[PDB]
Structure formats: structure tokens, C-alpha cells
Image: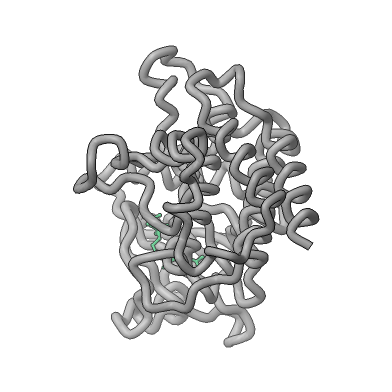
């Protein structure tokens, strides 16, 4: 993992010019830049050392990503703790977050098979975190803004500041059992799956009481046989009956009340690949 000068960070971002800002996260501003003389596109996150939750996330993202390698995980090229700063350098994901392609957006809608393949890609990332590191990693922050898309539309998991060895995605059993297991990532992923299908936020505080949380609302409509009515309008008529059923029953199991009843990510990943095959 590469240490960067604070001078290279300025060279890459052209001294943090707002022409290169990509957005704002809970950590700071995210800048697009180039390093190694313009062969490498990157994204650079500037955090604030005054905040020690920011300090905690900066060090956690470094100690996690520096030892992980997976096609479906955002890669951390390097960092900069110079002059008591806090900077992280990732590879640039040219197509932003998954949420920017589902709703509240001007981007075109994604075809069903591309959505399915994005969820499969993210499930592979999560499966690696749970079974491929030295110990289980619990991401704790699985959501549609933390799934990024590169120039070939490969889905990649990011945002490791809260991981250990958001509202609407929170494992409700965590506020009861007060323990945390990788099944909490499965809960959050099941919500991602429903967002991909319904193209609406996980929490929409303005709706009728039963519709506020996608996690409780989508299962409810499936049992009542009206899940087809809240499906993304672009997707209506584009999912074969058997894919629709395997997909929805996979998402329903992910958001069960009790973590012990939920599938593992290996199981989820397998059932999504099965769904893709039933679609074709
Ligand atoms: N590696 C990246 N490549 C491209 N754009 C990125 C990358 N990381 C973050 N972004 C952009 O920066 C924005 C801020 O994301 P992030 O800093 O993770 O904050 P949060 O996860 O709290 O929304 C994202 O919405 C996205 O547009």
C-alpha cells in the first residue's frame, strides 16, 4: 500500500479544484485525479483529522483494504497521512454508484440482466468478505450508494470505515439481540436486491405506514401476491416468471427477522446465478 506526498495529491487533483469534485460523503469531498503522469485515473477522498470517528474510519479502511484483493471490491491504491492530513486514493469508478442508476436520476434505466449481473457482482464481493479473508469481515454498511460501477459496469463493494472482524438497511435484529454477525450484511443485501427490483429508496418517510420500509413492504406484497405492482415500471414484462420467483424468494429470505434463518452469502450468490439462468 502506497504512501503519497501531499504534493502528489495536489498534482493529481490540481490542488483540489472544484472542477474535479465528484461528490460529498460522510468522510469529506471526493476528487477525481490522475497519478503516474496520467496513466491512472483515481478518486481521492480528503477526510478531517479533527474528527476521530473520521480518524477511526481512515485507519479501518486502510487496515482492511491493504490486505484484500478481489475483482468485486473497490481497490485502495494508497493514502496520505502527511502534515497530519487524512487522504485515501481509490481507483476511479466511472459510472458512479448503483443508486444513481435506479432512481432520482436522469441516467437511463438499466435492463434487467445488467441489474441482475450487478447484484451477482456485489454478492461475490460480499461472499469474499465473509469467506476469503483471514477472518470473517462484516462490512456493516451494505447499501446501493456503496456499490460502485466501473467503466465496464463491473459492480464493486466500497466504504469499509465501519467494518469489523444507514437507515432502511439496518439489521432490525441488531437492536434486539445486540450481537452482530455476517447475517446482518445478508439483511442489508436483501434490501439492495429489493431496490434493484423496485427502483425506490429503502426508506421513504412520506408514505403510508406499511410502505415506509422496502424491507417490510416488499415481502408483504409478495405474500399478498401484489409484488408485481411495486416493481420498477421499466422492468414490467421483462422478468420471466421463474426468475422473478427465484429472485424474490431469495430477497425475502435475506430480510427475515432472525439472522439464524437467513441464508449465507454463498447461498444468495448461488440463487442469483440460478435466477440469471432462469431468465435465459
Ligand atoms: N472510487 C470512486 N470512483 C468514482 N466515484 C467515486 C468513488 N468513490 C466515491 N465516488 C463518488 O463520491 C461520492 C461520495 O461517496 P462516498 O465518499 O463513499 O460517500 P457516501 O458513501 O457517504 O455517500 C459517491 O456518490 C460517488 O459519486
Most distant residue in the front direction: 225
Q: Quadrant of the C terminus?
A: bottom right
Find residue 24 and report its image quarter: bottom left
Could you tell me residue 127's position as x and y percent? 70, 41
Residue 234 seen in the figure: yes
Find residue 150 and report its image quarter: bottom right
Please name the residue shown 49% across and 73% down the image: 109
Could you tell me residue 52's position as x and y percent? 31, 39
Horizontal placement of 17 versus 192: left or right? Answer: left
Q: Quadrant of the N terminus?
A: bottom right
Please name the residue shown 44% across and 29% down the image: 171
- The colour scheme used here is one colour
The residue lying toward the viewer, choosing from 246 and 168, is 246
Could you tell me residue 40's position as x and y percent? 61, 79
* Ligand 1: image quarter: bottom left
Please name the residue shown 42% across and 43% down the image: 57
Horizontal placement of 101 versus 40: left or right? Answer: left
Please name the residue shown 27% across and 44% down the image: 51
- Above or below residue 61? Residue 174 is above
The residue lying toward the viewer, choosing from 160 and 85, is 160
- Above or below residue 203? Residue 277 is below
Residue 75 seen in the figure: no
The residue lying toward the viewer, choosing from 122 and 261, is 261
Could you tell me residue 185's position as x and y percent? 54, 35
Most distant residue in the left direction: 206
The residue lying toward the viewer, choosing from 165 and 225, is 225
Amino acid at each position: 500500500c502506497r504512501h503519497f506526498s501531499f504534493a502528489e495529491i495536489k498534482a493529481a487533483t490540481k490542488n483540489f479544484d472544484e472542477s474535479r469534485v465528484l461528490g460529498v460523503g460522510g468522510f469529506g469531498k471526493v476528487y477525481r485525479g490522475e497519478i503516474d503522469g496520467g496513466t491512472t485515473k483515481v478518486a481521492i477522498k480528503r477526510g478531517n483529522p479533527m474528527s476521530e470517528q473520521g480518524v477511526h474510519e481512515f485507519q479501518t479502511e486502510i487496515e482492511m483494504l491493504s490486505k484484500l484483493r478481489h475483482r468485486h471490491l473497490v481497490s485502495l491504491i494508497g493514502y496520505c497521512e502527511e502534515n497530519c492530513e487524512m487522504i485515501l486514493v481509490y481507483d476511479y469508478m466511472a459510472h458512479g454508484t448503483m443508486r444513481e442508476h435506479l432512481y432520482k436520476t436522469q441516467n437511463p434505466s438499466l435492463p434487467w440482466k445488467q441489474r441482475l449481473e450487478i447484484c451477482i457482482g456485489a454478492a461475490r464481493g460480499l461472499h469474499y468478505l465473509h469467506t476469503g479473508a483471514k477472518h470473517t469481515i462484516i462490512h456493516r454498511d451494505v447499501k446501493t450508494t456503496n456499490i460502485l460501477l466501473d467503466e465496464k459496469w463491473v459492480a464493486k463493494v466500497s466504504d469499509f470505515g465501519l467494518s469489523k472482524t444507514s437507515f432502511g438497511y439496518l439489521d432490525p435484529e441488531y437492536f434486539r439481540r445486540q450481537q452482530l454477525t455476517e447475517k446482518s450484511d445478508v439483511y442489508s443485501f436483501g434490501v439492495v436486491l429489493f431496490e434493484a427490483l423496485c427502483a425506490r429508496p429503502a426508506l421513504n418517510p412520506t408514505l403510508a405506514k406499511e410502505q415506509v420500509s422496502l424491507a417490510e413492504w416488499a415481502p408483504y406484497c409478495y405474500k399478498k401476491g401484489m409484488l408485481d405492482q411495486i416493481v420498477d415500471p421499466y422492468l414490467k414484462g421483462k422478468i420471466t416468471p421463474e426468475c422473478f420467483k427465484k429472485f424474490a424468494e431469495t430477497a425475502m429470505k435475506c430480510v427475515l427477522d432472525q439472522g439464524i434463518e437467513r441464508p449465507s452469502m454463498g447461498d444468495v450468490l448461488w440463487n442469483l446465478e440460478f435466477a440469471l439462468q432462469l431468465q435465459e
